[PDB]
Image 1 (cartoon, rainbow, N blue to C red):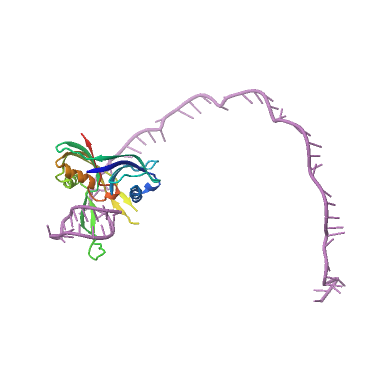
Image 2: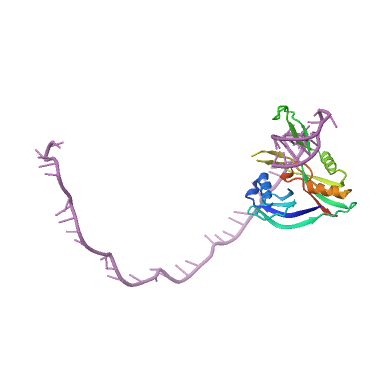
Length: 191
RNA sequence: AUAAACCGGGCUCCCUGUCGGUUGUAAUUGAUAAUGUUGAGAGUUCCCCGCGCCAGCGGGG
């Protein structure tokens, strides 16, 4: 039930695209992160939960850092923040084809607010109950030796805890696809 | 293989010493950038793997 929480910046040099953000992060030490200021002159402000202590490098400067244990009392309401990409997985309507030889599957984003909220309450399950949520819409992110696109949503709001351990390893494992591209990290805060 | 052939114009040498370009000088008065406008709609998001009851669900990029 332990972790390392850090405030990390990545020089705008490498931070030009997601792939190099995740790279720059890897070279500090798995882990999870939330982008807080994507493109400043100094570079890119990122919050970082991890299992290992980070050590500042030429590309990714560690501002401040501290180690944390989780003690959450069930029944207590909390503020939360989560950046993630709600999806549905279907079979291609373009009827494109897989490598093995039958048709491809595609992850499409959920584009209705109700569906997104639903997706949230679903994924956190009986760990907590969302009491108040606002599903912040974000501009799509692309990435470039692979290449594609992911559509994120940023939930902020108020949950009530129902099962502390469950919730805790939700926090430590992450919620939703695309963990290595800014998603997953759930941050909690006292009411 | 020609008024041709063979066939050096060649040796020595400070241009040197002296020298304020200097005093004086508002660029200054006048001047709306102003009228008019849903961002709406839309689940395609590219690769690997697991589970699938083929509705999809999940892990990793």
